Image 1 (cartoon, helix red, strand yellow):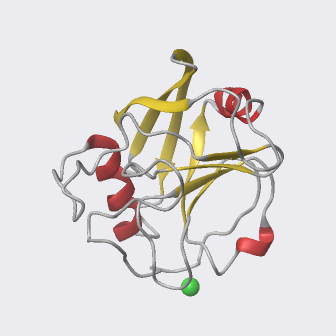
Image 2 (cartoon, rainbow, N blue to C red):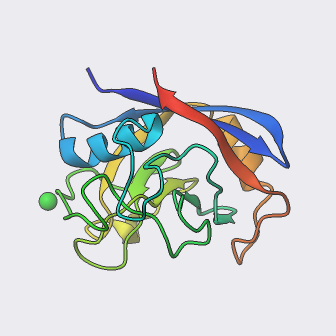
Length: 170
Ligand SMILES: [Cl-]
């Protein structure tokens, strides 16, 4: 009874595969619900007047041996995004930790500023523990994550556009 959601990814417009994620609704239900709803689009419109939906959004930064950073569906550059609760929402808890590749964690701009931006880790990032809320994990498609990672760079700039071409709940 953890929900599962997915991204179908394109690289330069072409399918790269599917990433399937399990969400820790048992541990961080409010955070999991935000992410689940951003996958389905079911809540409609955000504060921005744009759809609360990851579909069509790009990864703004992809950093080899660190993580993929995405979820800015209003600007695609790491300065936008919003949650189903409004512009920001509180840090629910820090129970789950950044233990390795496949960890799903919320990006933020300090305490209690969760929106829609998220991280998919490609390494163990323990220094983020207690600062970023971990709310799930990749359960299928780490090879897709690796393919995306290879289009990244140290600055995070991608050599081809990395887009969530479709998403939803399974
Ligand atoms: Cl905590």
